[PDB]
Image (spheres, rainbow, N blue to C red):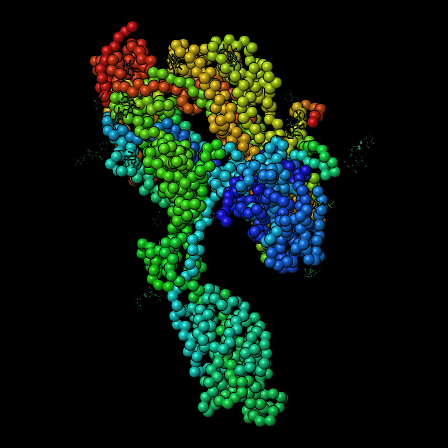
Amino acid sequence: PAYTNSFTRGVYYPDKVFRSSVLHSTQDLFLPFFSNVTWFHAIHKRFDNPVLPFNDGVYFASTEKSNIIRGWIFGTTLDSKTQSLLIVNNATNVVIKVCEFQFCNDPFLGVYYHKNNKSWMESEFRVYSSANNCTFEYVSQGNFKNLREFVFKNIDGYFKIYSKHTPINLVRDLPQGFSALEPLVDLPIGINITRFQTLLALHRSYYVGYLQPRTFLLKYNENGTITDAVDCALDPLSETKCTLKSFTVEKGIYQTSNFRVQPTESIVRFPNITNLCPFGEVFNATRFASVYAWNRKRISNCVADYSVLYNSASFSTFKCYGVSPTKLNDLCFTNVYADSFVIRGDEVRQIAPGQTGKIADYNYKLPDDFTGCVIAWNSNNLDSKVGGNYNYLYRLFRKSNLKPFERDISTEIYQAGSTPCNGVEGFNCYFPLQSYGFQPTNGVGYQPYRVVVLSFELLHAPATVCGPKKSTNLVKNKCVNFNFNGLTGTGVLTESNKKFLPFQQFGRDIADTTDAVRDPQTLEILDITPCSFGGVSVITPGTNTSNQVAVLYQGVNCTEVPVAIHNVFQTRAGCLIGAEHVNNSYECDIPIGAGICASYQTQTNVASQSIIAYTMSLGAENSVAYSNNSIAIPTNFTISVTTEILPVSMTKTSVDCTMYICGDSTECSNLLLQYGSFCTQLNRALTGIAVEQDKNTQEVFAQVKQIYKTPPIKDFGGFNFSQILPDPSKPSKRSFIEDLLFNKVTLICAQKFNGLTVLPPLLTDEMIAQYTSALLAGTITSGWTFGAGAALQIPFAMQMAYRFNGIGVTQNVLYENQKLIANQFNSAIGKIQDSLSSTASALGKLQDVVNQNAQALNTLVKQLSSNFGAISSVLNDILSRLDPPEAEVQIDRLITGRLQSLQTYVTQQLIRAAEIRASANLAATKMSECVLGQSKRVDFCGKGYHLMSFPQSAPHGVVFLHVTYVPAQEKNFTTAPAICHDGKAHFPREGVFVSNGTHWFVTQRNFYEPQIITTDNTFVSGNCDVVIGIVNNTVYDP
Amino acid sequence: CTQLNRALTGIAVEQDKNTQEVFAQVKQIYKTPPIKDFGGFNFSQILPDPSKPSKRSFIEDLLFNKVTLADAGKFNGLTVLPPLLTDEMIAQYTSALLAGTITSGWTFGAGAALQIPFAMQMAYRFNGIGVTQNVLYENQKLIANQFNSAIGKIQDSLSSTASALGKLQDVVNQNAQ
Amino acid sequence: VTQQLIRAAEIRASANLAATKMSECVLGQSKRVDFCGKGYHLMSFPQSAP
Amino acid sequence: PFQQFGRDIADTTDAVRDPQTLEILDITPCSFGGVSVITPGTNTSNQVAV
Amino acid sequence: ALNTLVKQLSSNFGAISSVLNDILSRLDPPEAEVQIDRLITGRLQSLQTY
Ligand SMILES: *[C@@H]1O[C@H](CO)[C@@H](O[C@@H]2O[C@H](CO)[C@@H](O[C@@H]3O[C@H](CO[C@H]4O[C@H](CO)[C@@H](O)[C@H](O)[C@@H]4O)[C@@H](O)[C@H](O[C@H]4O[C@H](CO)[C@@H](O)[C@H](O)[C@@H]4O)[C@@H]3O)[C@H](O)[C@H]2NC(C)=O)[C@H](O)[C@H]1NC(C)=O
Ligand SMILES: *[C@@H]1O[C@H](CO)[C@@H](O[C@@H]2O[C@H](CO)[C@@H](O[C@@H]3O[C@H](CO[C@H]4O[C@H](CO)[C@@H](O)[C@H](O)[C@@H]4O)[C@@H](O)[C@H](O)[C@@H]3O)[C@H](O)[C@H]2NC(C)=O)[C@H](O)[C@H]1NC(C)=O
Ligand SMILES: *[C@@H]1O[C@H](CO)[C@@H](O[C@@H]2O[C@H](CO)[C@@H](O[C@@H]3O[C@H](CO)[C@@H](O)[C@H](O)[C@@H]3O)[C@H](O)[C@H]2NC(C)=O)[C@H](O)[C@H]1NC(C)=O
Ligand SMILES: *[C@@H]1O[C@H](CO)[C@@H](O[C@@H]2O[C@H](CO)[C@@H](O[C@@H]3O[C@H](CO)[C@@H](O)[C@H](O)[C@@H]3O)[C@H](O)[C@H]2NC(C)=O)[C@H](O)[C@H]1NC(C)=O
Ligand SMILES: *[C@@H]1O[C@H](CO)[C@@H](O[C@@H]2O[C@H](CO)[C@@H](O[C@@H]3O[C@H](CO)[C@@H](O)[C@H](O)[C@@H]3O)[C@H](O)[C@H]2NC(C)=O)[C@H](O)[C@H]1NC(C)=O
Ligand SMILES: *[C@@H]1O[C@H](CO[C@@H]2O[C@@H](C)[C@@H](O)[C@@H](O)[C@@H]2O)[C@@H](O[C@@H]2O[C@H](CO)[C@@H](O)[C@H](O)[C@H]2NC(C)=O)[C@H](O)[C@H]1NC(C)=O
Ligand SMILES: *[C@@H]1O[C@H](CO)[C@@H](O[C@@H]2O[C@H](CO)[C@@H](O)[C@H](O)[C@H]2NC(C)=O)[C@H](O)[C@H]1NC(C)=O
Ligand SMILES: *[C@@H]1O[C@H](CO)[C@@H](O[C@@H]2O[C@H](CO)[C@@H](O)[C@H](O)[C@H]2NC(C)=O)[C@H](O)[C@H]1NC(C)=O
Ligand SMILES: *[C@@H]1O[C@H](CO)[C@@H](O[C@@H]2O[C@H](CO)[C@@H](O)[C@H](O)[C@H]2NC(C)=O)[C@H](O)[C@H]1NC(C)=O
Ligand SMILES: *[C@@H]1O[C@H](CO)[C@@H](O[C@@H]2O[C@H](CO)[C@@H](O)[C@H](O)[C@H]2NC(C)=O)[C@H](O)[C@H]1NC(C)=O
Ligand SMILES: *[C@@H]1O[C@H](CO)[C@@H](O)[C@H](O)[C@H]1NC(C)=O
Ligand SMILES: *[C@@H]1O[C@H](CO)[C@@H](O)[C@H](O)[C@H]1NC(C)=O
Ligand SMILES: *[C@@H]1O[C@H](CO)[C@@H](O)[C@H](O)[C@H]1NC(C)=O
Ligand SMILES: *[C@@H]1O[C@H](CO)[C@@H](O)[C@H](O)[C@H]1NC(C)=O
Ligand SMILES: *[C@@H]1O[C@H](CO)[C@@H](O)[C@H](O)[C@H]1NC(C)=O
Ligand SMILES: *[C@@H]1O[C@H](CO)[C@@H](O)[C@H](O)[C@H]1NC(C)=O
């Protein structure tokens, strides 16, 4: 009876929506894969009646053997009240009928073994008893066999079926295959299902799975068909794929979620037990009051658990109104009156809001809206006293009815008619007092039900007379909230190391947050520290590498599920899991937090798949003489094409406010124009954006006052750049690398989708390419002059010879090694095409920028789906739903939320545009200062220095293929600051006197071309009498 | 909050990139040389003194003490994250860049840390503002003396004055508030 | 959040300026006169700050 | 067969299928675009353009 | 922009005067409190915008 496993199977279709080579993650009922399943037995005599609940759906699959299983009973509970889905199955077909099911023990069918010729299997047939509600009655359509598979979901009765017809080649358990399960029919029925019961045809009396609100990331095909499916949290690489929406993820930490932990919830605490609440002497008093003379005494500044008097075992009646008497202590009140007096026993009923009697008539009135509890308590063996307990009187005469809780004690000469008494009573002069008269042998009606009234007087006065709610043992060192009489917060409540004062009850920090609390029940002190918080961003590589993740926790004290099936190396960033520690700190790959980078590794020696981390150290410290002597100057150099990329513009999304909002709706436009101005200011601000980056595009591209055509005579002399010059043989006049880039960059994709009014660029593809061509032609062949007014041609053999000296290098090294320079220039171009064909890392940020453009448009459109109290993306349905007056009063706040959504969106648009203008003036800086010339200022035009950059086409962007001089050797040798000959120092303004020790020579500050000391290069200036570490040398004249 | 989570991730990327091209431009995480032979260029207040196990210096402590009132810096929604480069090794970066300009001079960024002597590195420094390095060779010991005095006056403006602390205090306090 | 993003914009512009200071002003000397502080600029010593 | 609706990369209405017949359709917003009027200065006469 | 800052007072959201004090005086002090609640929320919108 062992259990089994499932790999990936059981994926359905969301709805009839048709997609095309896209990646959606729409959330609905889902099937967790790698989830526990069961392998049953087939007849070879067990009943095989797997009857489970339909919790969130059921995953099913089977292989038929002899057309055995056909009986299903899908229902809620089957108490002869809920429906059931009868099923029939011929050879390769389906059919569903739904109505009732009433059978006991084992419902099933039976195919006999020793059948002489045939059989029919309908004798037992515990299938139907009274098919009296069959609405959705829809009828239509030797080794191992094929496979069947059914999945469903519970959406308002939509028991939608999904089926597939293909065989499998696994006879033991689930196949090692993967496929979708397309919907066949969605019956509506109308009675839900939570319990599914099945029956089958066996002589004597099939996987089962379960669904949950899981998550998925689908990947369809160009035929619009499901290919695979992945959850998110099941293996955190899947979380990475979900948050990045791709099945081929590069390695990196991707924020997953937080974790709102709350161990042992929170502790509720009130001060120590009441003080100056002697309820006994008021309620078990020898001295009570009369009904018309009811006493009135307060209880204050001491708490009352209204349940301790309940369990004090001293009453016979417990009636409380308004608020819950049970555990009423947790509620805190202004003040309470606890009064005791005596009335007739039968009158407990009469003691309530609105009840009547002689008590209410002349003795004691109760408010209709009473705010209190009422209790009566019996002492029947003590309610009478020898000599009779008639001490407490009651009133028989009163002209006026009492006001709420009014007390009448006056016993003046009572007058009833208009004939007076003159102070002496008698006939028509009625005595107003009579006594109770409690006798030991009196009947139950006069046998007292002695009542006590508890009134909670909740005026505007402060509520501090309260009840002890739940004062329990202090929770030490368990992250919990607290309830100190009204204040809460996740606290590390333990003994705290500070001094406290009588004024101290609650405390804040400089940031006004609870950092210390105080024990109200006794002299004890507590502190609070933020216990866990922290989000999760998983450090795992992508689907190309293994699926073994590593998970990091952000600044949270190791108090949540240590390493297990659910290692640990604690860091300043928090508790790290899923990655064992490594002593050595490699070169970083992916920072996670507190400067730790983790790379998956395999320690071949058995095969373990675990990720390893380390700390921040690019190699180690470099050990060279740093005090006074060692000087390092490269005898060799390289030219790496530092392909940095700058976003020159942005999609000119000149949104049309009204038409973006109010499409085919005059009511919407009418209501918007009441707000009016706003969206118009948004509109022309966006147009100002458009003109801003179009001017950027101009001055970065049409900085020349003239359109220029590249010369068709490619005599550049062995240095060529044909992959960057537009070859005159293509329909789009962009060169090779533009082709590769534009193939690499994709995804908005057109100007004709929606209210997303994509304006065409002020420079379209062919003519933005024309500008790029013009720029490259100039900066290669005429240069600054054609970029700064009148053209003057210049060969590239001089265009860069100038700019070595523009950096510090000398054009002599060009003349001496330029054939190689060109060869490695072509090598750099090859590196371009290679590392930019499919490798997106180098070409990253331009594509990235057009991304946040794309999902900016995407949040702009699906912001409509963010219905701000609406029931749709666009109110068009709601627009037609209500009367234009009612439409006015609803679209008012609804489309007001929509326009503030627009304002938000365009605000991120403004900010994005702001950093784009920053980057765009930066692009102008690059182009003008560095390509129409050269930024002599060090290392600003990409890593290393800068010689050329070649403007190559990019949607709203550009790449500047810097030709940077980069050192390659460490001649880290002894030094000489100057040449003390006879008290004077020989030195050029640039250069350093350098030697390994053989010959002290002068050489340039970035290239090791040593030279003889000469009076021309080395010219005497000042003296050398103040130096730190000089050595002498001779001087010669060539 | 989806887009704002994106925005805060953008904030993280911008800040640690700021760190990168401000600190982690180094191609080799780096530490100070053992000996200190410079020519009067006392760096105790600035360079991480190997005396303290932590690699900070006097002005680091002065900065910390002057702006201890960092308020948050945590409790309620204050989901502050520690720097992707910790304080101790961001100080290691401070040292790295320090010794880098000390030794590999301005050539540092061009690749390998091609070290050059600091004292004669100032020669390129004087030549970097149009004054010939002869003045270095003619008065540089004194140059160092009043340079050290200038650093001491900086420390004075750090401790007995808040002029050197002004807009740091403003930015941290405005973040705090 | 918008205020924080905007402040991020200005501070990050200042931060690119900081990188430029690192480059033309620490990893190099700004031939561009008198922006690295009053007077001229030779070089600078970076140091930590919160 | 199970499909009836349509979508596109930007998750907006791209194609629909006729419930009464099988036909591979497309939908595109009508014209939009814009109206930017070109004209010389009004010191020059009223020869207009759209 | 200054003229805007002035003229969204015309953008009166459901009121019919520039400065809202007369609308406040136009309704009963509780009812005026209710209406001025959302006039002032709109005014805060205008503030944060500007
Ligand atoms: C909805 O359901 C109704 C049910 O009747 C369909 O009506 C029939 O539809 C079929 C095909 O859909 C019609 O067949 C027609 O064939 C014509 C070709 O003519 C040759 O073949 C006939 C076959 O009998 C010969 O008799 C004749 O001499 C010719 O040799 C086509 O020209 C017809 O096309 C028309 O209908 C289709 C839609 O079906 C339109 O798209 C066309 O533009 C054109 O208008 C048609 O294919 C049959 O005649 C119909 N009979 C009746 C009684 O209606 C509807 O067609 C169906 N809806 C759709 C969209 O198919
Ligand atoms: C997406 O939907 C498209 C629309 O149908 C699919 O296009 C179909 O593609 C198939 C093959 O790719 C074409 O099949 C034709 O079959 C005939 C005869 O079949 C013989 O040859 C095959 C081997 O190809 C053999 O296995 C058979 O047993 C037969 O002996 C061939 O002569 C044709 O060359 C062609 O292969 C369909 O015609 C074509 N549908 C059309 C044109 O309407 C496409 O395949 C779908 N996508 C995927 C991934 O399947
Ligand atoms: C309210 O809460 C409790 C209730 O008594 C008080 O703390 C408890 O009492 C005293 C301290 O007040 C602790 O010492 C104990 O005293 C008793 C009585 O003398 C003695 O018999 C014991 O041997 C012990 O010494 C007692 O331990 C403590 N309870 C616990 C669990 O530690 C508290 O002081 C009260 N505060 C007020 C303001 O009433
Ligand atoms: C030029 O630079 C290289 C590295 O950039 C220098 O190599 C390094 O030299 C130092 C000492 O000169 C080495 O430190 C010592 O190395 C010995 C043996 O290698 C070891 O036994 C000591 O414990 C100490 O570590 C260092 O290892 C070595 N390699 C590095 C730093 O990667 C080279 O010496 C420099 N050239 C000159 C002329 O100094
Ligand atoms: C560069 O700067 C440091 C900064 O601390 C300087 O440290 C100085 O070191 C000297 C001795 O090494 C200290 O001199 C003192 O002399 C008295 C005379 O009796 C003696 O009792 C003291 O114990 C101490 O030796 C001097 O106070 C100290 N200065 C400071 C500000 O701490 C030093 O000039 C240089 N350090 C180097 C090059 O390592
Ligand atoms: C569906 O049909 C049922 C009829 O079956 C009844 O309920 C079974 C549990 C069993 O007791 C049969 O013998 C019954 O005949 C409808 O059930 C009754 O419907 C009437 C009104 O139509 C209602 O007054 C009764 O309370 C229902 N229950 C019973 C036990 O009589 C049921 O209404 C039909 N519709 C739905 C949606 O279930
Ligand atoms: C095959 O499936 C269909 C429903 O999906 C059913 O077919 C019925 O078969 C019987 C017996 O041959 C016929 O009398 C009926 O006329 C068929 N139905 C229809 C609508 O024509 C049945 O469930 C399956 N066939 C069998 C034999 O069980
Ligand atoms: C839908 O499923 C529920 C789950 O039991 C069925 O039960 C009743 O559900 C309604 C509202 O969902 C409750 O008010 C009742 O108290 C539930 N009754 C019981 C006994 O639990 C419900 O009957 C199902 N729907 C239909 C139409 O039958
Ligand atoms: C500078 O280094 C480059 C390689 O980085 C050298 O180019 C090689 O030179 C040798 C002989 O000079 C040739 O045999 C190789 O074919 C060259 N290319 C390589 C190795 O890829 C260059 O020579 C060096 N500079 C000097 C002056 O020698
Ligand atoms: C200029 O660069 C181009 C690069 O496109 C070189 O063109 C190659 O020429 C060879 C032989 O004629 C062809 O096999 C290649 O297909 C061409 N294209 C390539 C490699 O992309 C051309 O050789 C270069 N010219 C000089 C003088 O070096
Ligand atoms: C899954 O199956 C294994 C087989 O032993 C079993 O141990 C485990 O408890 C099952 N898990 C659940 C809860 O389904
Ligand atoms: C977590 O907090 C407890 C509080 O007592 C402390 O003892 C423990 O060392 C802390 N662990 C870490 C490293 O967070
Ligand atoms: C870890 O690496 C350091 C590096 O110096 C070394 O000193 C130490 O011995 C190593 N320890 C282990 C356990 O590998
Ligand atoms: C040492 O100096 C000699 C000069 O004779 C030079 O050729 C050699 O390259 C130097 N050593 C190194 C490692 O460069
Ligand atoms: C550099 O300093 C070391 C140690 O102080 C010394 O041995 C060496 O001679 C010095 N060299 C120069 C040129 O000052
Ligand atoms: C309008 O003004 C422009 C401004 O220079 C001038 O060139 C043009 O000739 C004027 N035309 C008329 C008709 O006034």
Residue B174, visible in the rendered structure:
no
Between A153 and D8, which is closer to the camera in this rendering? A153
Between A563 and B87, which is closer to the camera in this rendering? A563
Q: Is residue A827 above or below residue A258?
A: above
State the residue lying farthest toward the front.
A116
Return the x and y of residue D38 as percentages of the image width and height: 66, 25
Residue A808 in which image quadrant: top left
Q: Is residue A430 above or below residue A314?
A: below
* Residue displayed at 51% across by 41% down: A232
Between A258 and A547, which is closer to the camera in this rendering? A547
Return the x and y of residue A549 as percentages of the image width and height: 44, 38
* Residue displayed at 41% across by 32% down: A589
Residue A347 in which image quadrant: bottom right
Q: Is residue A358 left or right of residue A99?
A: left
Q: Is residue A466 left or right of residue A8?
A: left
Query: Image quadrant for the C terminus of chain A?
Result: top left
